[PDB]
Amino acid sequence: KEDYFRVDMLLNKKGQVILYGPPGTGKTWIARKYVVEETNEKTPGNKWEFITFHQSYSYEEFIEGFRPRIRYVVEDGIFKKIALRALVKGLFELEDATIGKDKIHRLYILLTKKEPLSPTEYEEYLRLKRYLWELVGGLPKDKLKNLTPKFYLIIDEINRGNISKIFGELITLLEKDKRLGGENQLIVRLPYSGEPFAVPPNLYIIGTMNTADRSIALLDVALRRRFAFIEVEPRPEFLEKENLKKIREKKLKTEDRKRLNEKLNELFSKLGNDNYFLKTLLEKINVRITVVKDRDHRIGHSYFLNVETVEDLHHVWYYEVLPLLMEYFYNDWETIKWVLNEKGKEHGNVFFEKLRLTGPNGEEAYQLKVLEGDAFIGALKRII
Amino acid sequence: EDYFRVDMLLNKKGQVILYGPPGTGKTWIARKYVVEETNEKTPGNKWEFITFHQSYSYEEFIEGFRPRIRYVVEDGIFKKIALRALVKGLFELEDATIGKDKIHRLYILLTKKEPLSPTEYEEYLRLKRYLWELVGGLPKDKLKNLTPKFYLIIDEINRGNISKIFGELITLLEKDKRLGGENQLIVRLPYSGEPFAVPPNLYIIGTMNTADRSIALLDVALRRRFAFIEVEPRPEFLEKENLKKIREKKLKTEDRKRLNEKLNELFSKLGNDNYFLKTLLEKINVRITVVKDRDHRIGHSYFLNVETVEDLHHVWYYEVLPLLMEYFYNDWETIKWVLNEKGKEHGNVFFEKLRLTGPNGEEAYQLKVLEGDAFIGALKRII
Amino acid sequence: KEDYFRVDMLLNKKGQVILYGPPGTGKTWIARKYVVEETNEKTPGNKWEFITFHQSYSYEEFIEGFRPRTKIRYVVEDGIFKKIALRALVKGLFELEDATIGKDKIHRLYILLTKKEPLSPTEYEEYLRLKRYLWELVGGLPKDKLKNLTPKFYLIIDEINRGNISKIFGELITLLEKDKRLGGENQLIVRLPYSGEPFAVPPNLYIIGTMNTADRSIALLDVALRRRFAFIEVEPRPEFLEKENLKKIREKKLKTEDRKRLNEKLNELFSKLGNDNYFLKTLLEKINVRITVVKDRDHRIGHSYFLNVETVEDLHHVWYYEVLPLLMEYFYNDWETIKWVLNEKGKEHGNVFFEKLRLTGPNGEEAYQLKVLEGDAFIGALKRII
Amino acid sequence: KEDYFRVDMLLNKKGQVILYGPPGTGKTWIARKYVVEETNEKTPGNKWEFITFHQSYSYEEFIEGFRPRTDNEEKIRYVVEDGIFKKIALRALVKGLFELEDATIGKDKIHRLYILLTKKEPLSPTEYEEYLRLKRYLWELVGGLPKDKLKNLTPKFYLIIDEINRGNISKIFGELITLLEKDKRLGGENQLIVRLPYSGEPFAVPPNLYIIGTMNTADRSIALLDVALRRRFAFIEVEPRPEFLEKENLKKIREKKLKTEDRKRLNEKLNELFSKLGNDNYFLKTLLEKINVRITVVKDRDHRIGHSYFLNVETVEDLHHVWYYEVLPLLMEYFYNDWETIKWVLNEKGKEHGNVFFEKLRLTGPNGEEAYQLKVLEGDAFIGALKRII
Ligand SMILES: Nc1nc2c(ncn2[C@@H]2O[C@H](COP(=O)(O)OP(=O)(O)OP(O)(O)=S)[C@@H](O)[C@H]2O)c(=O)[nH]1
Ligand SMILES: Nc1nc2c(ncn2[C@@H]2O[C@H](COP(=O)(O)OP(=O)(O)OP(O)(O)=S)[C@@H](O)[C@H]2O)c(=O)[nH]1
Ligand SMILES: Nc1nc2c(ncn2[C@@H]2O[C@H](COP(=O)(O)OP(=O)(O)OP(O)(O)=S)[C@@H](O)[C@H]2O)c(=O)[nH]1
Ligand SMILES: Nc1nc2c(ncn2[C@@H]2O[C@H](COP(=O)(O)OP(=O)(O)OP(O)(O)=S)[C@@H](O)[C@H]2O)c(=O)[nH]1
Ligand SMILES: [Mg+2]
Ligand SMILES: [Mg+2]
Ligand SMILES: [Mg+2]
Ligand SMILES: [Mg+2]
C-alpha cells in the first residue's frame, strides 16, 4: 500500500489531491478503494460522495443555486451538502458546552434526509445553518482543527468540467490553511443565499483526471496550487504472471479461482513460457509511444488486466489497442509501424501489411492484417 | 462472423462501437444483432434506438430540468432505459429485501408512454429513491447477473459531443464499474440530486462514421470504455453468388427467381465475370486507401442494390462519381488515377480532357457520360 | 422528358435526391416542376412542402423543439419535417385496409396535422395521444403493408447546403436511407430526444434537395450524408440558347398571340448577332470552358442569365450588369485571368471589355478599367469571345 | 436622369438591384432619390422602407423571429414577430390585393390586415391572434388565385437596404435566396411559396415589392456574397464621378437645391475658391481623377475616393477639412502601415521634409524600422501640395 500511503499523506497535507495520468491506470480504482477502506462504507451516502464533472456541470449544482420547488429555494449543491455534513458530524464528536447537540443532531437529520425538504422544514434548515455558522467563529481554532470522522468527495474526470467556473469561492476556501481550524481560517459569504460558508478540515477531495486530452487538461496554476498531483503511471509489472494472478485473486476466493490460476498457465505457456510477456510488451509499447507522441498517451495497464486466454489478448489487441493506436497516428503509417517496430518489413506476419500499389505522387499505404494463433504471438514477440 | 464478435465484445466490455467508412453495414449489423437478441422488431420495451447529433445534450440524454408550472428533473433516454433495465433485472432476482410490488409499480411508471401526472411523478421519485436505497445494500454476486438483456443502439454516436452528452457515463459505463461489478460505482447526479449507476443488464452498440475527421472520436479516455469493431468494406458480398444470397435473404416469395435471371442478365453483360463488382470495389478501395485515408473507402451498400446494368450505371454516375469528385475537388490527376485513366485524356473515358488550356498552363477535364458497352469497357479498365 | 425521368428514377430508387450544380441551371426549376407534375398541386401544403435551408434553421425548427404555447405551457412542437412525415404516414394509412388500423382516429390525426390554426391546449394532448396510438400501430403492423403507401409526398429543400445539415438532420442521418424507412427490410424507429415520442420516415415521403456547388465553404464534405441522396449534376445547357430552343422555351408558358410577336423579337435579335442561331450557345460554351479551366467546373455561368434575352439591349444589360460583375467577383483584381476568359489577353485599348490604364505602379504592376461598349462594337467584342 | 432610368429598368427586369461602389459616390442618395421619385413620398412608412444591414443584423429581425412582448402589461413572452421584410412583403401583397378585381377576396378582411400591417405600435394579444388569422386567410387566398391576377399589382413597394454587404446576406435572407427571383415571386411562372421555420406559416414575395441595395465594395472583411446571391440581383457600378467637381458642375449641383438669394453668395464664394487653386475650374475634377487612377493601379478598383466628399466644398478651409478629415483617414485606412504606397498615390514618393502630407521622421529603429507622421499644411503650402498631385 504505497499509492494508498501517498494518497493518505497528501490528503493530510494539501487537503485535496488529483490523481492524474494516462487512461487505463488506476485512478478511479485507487480513489474508490481508498475511500471505501477509510470510511468503511462500500456505497456513497453520508460519509462520502462520488461525482463526475462534465461540461453540463455548473456552480449551481455544485455549491448552491436557485430552484423553483412557487418561490426560489436556494438549493445547496453536492459540495455544500457534504461540507455541512462533515462539519455537523465533526461537531458531534467535538465535546463543548456551546455546541448544542440537540440542534446539531436536527441539522444532521435535515442534511441526511434524502427526501426533498418541505417548506416547513426549509426554514428550519436555514435557521439551523445560521446557528451553525454563528456557532463556529466563536469556537476556538484548536478545537475546529481536529475533526475525527473524515468525509470524502471523489470528483472523477475533474478536468472535464470548467473547474474554475464550478469552484466558486472554493478557489480560496479549498486551501488547507484557509479551511476551518487552520491559522488563516476564512469563512466567506455566498451569493445566492448570503449565508457564510467555509470548507471544514473534515472533508477531503480526491480528483481523478486523464492527461491524454490536452484541450481539457488544466492549466490554471492558481487552481493547481490547491491540489497535490499524484501521477498514476502505467504499471506493466502488474501484467507479470504472478502479479496478474494475485490481482485476479481478489474477488476469487472459491474453487473457481482454481480454474483461474491454470487459465493463466495455458496463457503464458502459449506466449512462450514467458512470465514477462505482457509486462515487457506494454513496457516497449509505452516507451515507444512516449518518444513519438508524449508520455500522457501511454497505454494503461487495465487493457491487459482482464486477459486470461490468448483469444482475450487477441480481442484486447485488435479491438482496444490497435484502434487506439490508429486514432493516435491517423494515416501516419511509419510512426504506428515504428511503435510496433515493424518499420523495416512490409509483409509477412505483420499487423499492417503494405498494399502493392503506390500513389501517383509517390505515396504508399498499409492495411490492417488480422493475425490469429501462433502468428499473432509471433508478431507480438517482435515488439519485445 | 460479425454477429459472434459483437456478442463476444459486448459481454466483456459492456459497450461496442462499430466504426468504419460509410456504406459498410454497421447500423445494419447493430439492428440485426439487437432484433435477433431481443426477439422484437420494434424499439420500445427491451431495446431503444437513438441517433446522436449536435442537439443532443446531457439534459435530453441522462436528466435535465424541464418545466412540467413546476420545474421537474425529467430523466433522459439513458436514465429511462437504465432504470428500466435495472428494475426488469430486479424482477427475476429472488431475494427477501426486494419488495416486488414497488419494483413492479416502478416498471409500470418507467414503461408508461403517457406523460406522468404530478400525483404519479412524486410516486416515481419515491420508488426511484427506494430503488437506489435497495441496490446500495444488495450484494455484488446477486446484481452481477440480471436476467434479461437491454440494448441501446446509438447510431452515429460520434456526431454529438460524446464526452459532454455522456456526463456521468464516462465512469459508469465500464463493465468493472457497473452494478454488481468488482468496483461498483454509484454516482450522484447534479440535477436530481439522486444517485445513479448503470446496471450490467444494459448494453450499448454505437455506430460511427470515420470518414469525417471533424467528428472523430479523439477522446482517448472515452475509447477505453468501448470495444472498437471495424466494419470494413466487403467487396466479396458483390460476387454474383453472394449478391444472390444476400438479396434473397430479405424476400421469401416466388419472385426471387425474378431476382435470379435479372442477376444473370447483369453478369453476362459485365463480361461473364462473376467477380466484376467485387474486383471493381476492391480496386477502387485500394486506390482510395493509397491516395486518401483508409476510412474514405467506398462501402458495398452502393452496389448491393445493383440488379441490372442500368442500376449499376445510376449507382456509378449519381452516387460514387459525385462522391469521387467531392473527395478530390479540382484534383483531376488524383481522381484520374483512382479510375487508373491517368494517361487516357480522350476516348471512352469518364473524364475527357478539354482541348483548351489555361494561360498559366493549367488543364481541366470534363465529366463524360458513358452508356452501354462503352461504360462496361471503361469499368473493365479499372479492374 | 429526360431530366424529369432522371429525378423520377433516382427518387424512386433512392428516396432522396440532390440537384447540384452551378447557379442558374434550373435545379429549383426542375424540382418545383417535377413536384407540381407528380402531385397535381401548384401550391405547397397538402401533398408537398417547400422549405429553404440556411444558418438560422436548427433541429428545433426542422424536427421538433420546445416552444411556449398558451397560462403558458412548455410544449414540444414538431418542425416542418416531422409534420410532413407524420402527414405522409397518416395519409398513407388511409388507403391501407387492415383491422388494427382505427381509421376514425387516423382521420382525426390527419385533421390535426393539416390544421392551419395553432393547436388548442385541449386539442394538443389529443394530438399527442393520437401520435402515441399511431406509433403503437405502426410498430405492430407487418412490413409488407407499410412497404408501399398509396400517395406520394414531397419536400423540396432548396439551397440545402446553406444550412448545417448534419446538425439539422438529427436522426435523419439514419432514417432517410430507403432500407431504414417504414416497410423497408431494415426499418428503424428512432426515439427523439426532446419529446421522447418515436419517429420513422415513411416511404410516402420524398425529399428533394438542391445545392449550390459554386460556394466551397458550404459544400457537402460529410461523406455519410452523401450516401442517402442521389446526386444529379445539373450542368449549364447552352443548347437552350439557340434560336429554336429559345422559341420553344419562351413561347411555352404564354400560349397567347404574343408568340407571333415574340419570335419577331427573336428575329431582330439574332440578325443583330450576325444571323447566327448559335451565337449565345457558343458564347456560353466558350465562356464556361474558360471558367472550367481557370476555376473549378462548377463556378460556370448558368444558362438562366441568357434565357430572358430578347433584344440586343437585353443582352447588353445582362452582360454588363449580371455576368461581368460576376466575372469581376470570380477573379477579383486578377486582370490577366478575366481578360483571358474573354480571350482578349493580348488585346488592349480597342473595342475591348477591359481597357488598359496608361499608368503603371511603382512595383511595375498595372490595372485595367471596365469599358462600356454599345451598339455593334459590343457585338464585335462578343464575336471575339466565340 | 439616366442612372435613375438604369435603376428603373434593371429593377423592373430583375426585381432587385444593388448599387455597388466605393464610399462617397452617392449610392444611398441615388437609391433614396429614385424611391422618393417613384412613390412620391419624402419619408418611409407605408409604400417604402429603409434599413441598414450591420454586422449583428439577423434573420430573426428581418423575416421572423421570437421577439419578447408583454402580455396584458404584466409579463414578457417570446412570440414569433415578423421582421422588416415580411411586414413590408405582406403590406405590398395586401395593398396589391386592394386594387385587384376578384370575387374570392374578402376586402373587409384584407383591408383590416392592411391596418394590422400599418399601425406603428405593438400589437395587443387580443388583435395579434386576429393578425395571425388574417395572415392565414391571406395565404389561403393567394394559394388558389391564378397567375394572371397576381402578375400585375397596381402600386410599387420599395425596400432600400443601405450597406448591404455589412451583414451576412445569406444568413439574413434565408428563404429570400429562393424567393427573391422574379420568376419565383407571386404570379410569376415558377411561383414559389416557402414555409417559414419559426411561425410555421407560408410566405412568398409579391412582385409588388422591389429591393435597392447599396454595397460598399472598398472593405472586404465582410463583403463576400455568394454567387447564387449575385444571381438574384442586378449589379450597378456607381463609379466616383470627378466631373461632378468641375466649377460649373459643382455650381449646378449646389444650386439644384433651394436657394432664393444665396445662389449669388455661392457664386462669389466659389470664385474665391478656384482663384486660389490656380484659376483652374477643373482642379478638383482632375485631382480626383489623378488620385483615383493612382488608387486603381496599386489598390483595387473599388477602393477609390468618392466624389461627394468635395460636393460641400465651397471655401479653401472647407477643402482643407475635407482633405485632412475625410479622404486622408480613408487613404490611411486603406494603406495601413504601407507608407511608400500611400506616398505614391499622392506621388510625393521620395520627396520628404518639404511641403508634404506625410513627413518622414528623422529617427530609425533598431532593425531599420521606419515611420511617417501626418503633417498638417495650411495656407499656400497646402494648395501647393495639392497642385503636385496632378
Ligand atoms: N487490482 C487492481 N485493479 C486495477 C488496478 N488499476 C486498475 N485496475 C482495474 O482496471 C479498471 C480500470 O481502471 P480505472 O481506475 O477505472 O481507470 P481510470 O483511471 O479511471 O481511467 P480513466 O477514467 O482516466 S479513462 C478498474 O476497474 C480496476 O478494477 C490496480 O492497480 N489493481
Ligand atoms: N444482407 C446484408 N445487407 C447489408 C450488409 N451490409 C450492408 N447492408 C445493407 O446496406 C445498407 C447500408 O448499411 P448501413 O447499416 O445503413 O450502413 P451504415 O453503417 O449505417 O453507414 P453509415 O451510417 O456510417 S453512413 C443497409 O440498409 C443494409 O441493408 C450485409 O452485410 N448484409
Ligand atoms: N424551360 C426551362 N427554364 C429554365 C431552365 N433552367 C432555368 N430556367 C429558368 O431560369 C430561371 C432560373 O432557374 P432556377 O431554378 O432558379 O436555377 P437554379 O438552379 O435554382 O439556380 P440557383 O438557385 O442555384 S441560383 C427559372 O425560373 C426558369 O424559368 C430549364 O432547364 N428549362
Ligand atoms: N446633389 C447631390 N448630392 C449628392 C450626390 N451624391 C452624393 N450626394 C450627397 O452626398 C452625401 C453622401 O452620399 P451617400 O449617399 O451617403 O454616398 P454613399 O455611397 O452611401 O457613402 P457610404 O454610405 O458608402 S459611406 C449624401 O448626403 C448625398 O446627399 C449627387 O450626385 N448630387
Ligand atoms: Mg475513471
Ligand atoms: Mg448508420
Ligand atoms: Mg434555387
Ligand atoms: Mg450609404
Image (cartoon, coloured by chain):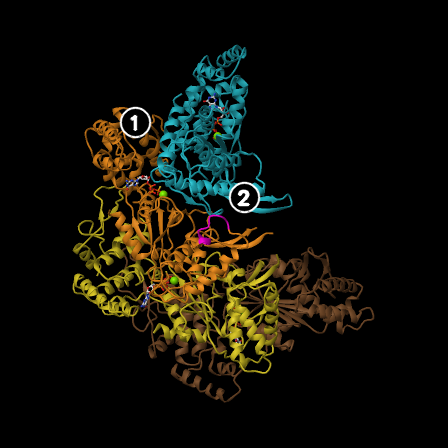
Chain colours: A brown, B yellow, C orange, D cyan
Against A116, residue D390 (above or below) is above
Q: Residue C313 carries which label?
A: 1
Q: Which residue is drawn at 53% across and 29% down?
A: D374
Q: Residue A135 carries which label?
A: none
Q: Circle 2 marks a residue in which chain?
A: D
Q: Mark 2 points at which residue?
A: D129
Please tell me whether residue C113 belongs to the stretch shown in magenta. Answer: yes
A270 vs A219, left or right, is: left
The answer to whether residue A146 is seen in the rendering is no
Q: Which of A266 and A121 lies nearest the eye of the viewer?
A: A121
CB at disc 2 and ligand 7 closer than 8 Å: no
Q: Residues within 10 Å of mark 2 (few under 14, many from 20)?
A: few
Nearer the observer: mark 2 or 1; the answer is: 2
CB at disc 1 and ligand 3 closer than 8 Å: no
Q: Dots 2 and 1: beta carbons under 8 Å?
A: no
Q: Give the range drawn in magenta.
A: C111-118
B135 vs C238, left or right, is: right
Magenta stretch, main secondary structure, is loop
Mark 2 to mark 1 CA distance (whole Å): 50 Å
The percent position of residue A284, horizontal first and vertical second, equals 43, 72
Tell me the element at label 2: helix
Question: How many numbered dots are placed on residues in this image?
Answer: 2
Q: Which of D307 and C72 lies nearest the eye of the viewer?
A: C72
Q: Circle 1 marks a residue in which chain?
A: C
**Within the displayed image, which quadrant is ligand 2 positioned in?**
bottom left
A188 vs B188, left or right, is: right
The percent position of residue A17, horizontal first and vertical second, equals 61, 67
**Amino acid type, label 1:** Glu
The answer to whether residue D294 is seen in the rendering is yes
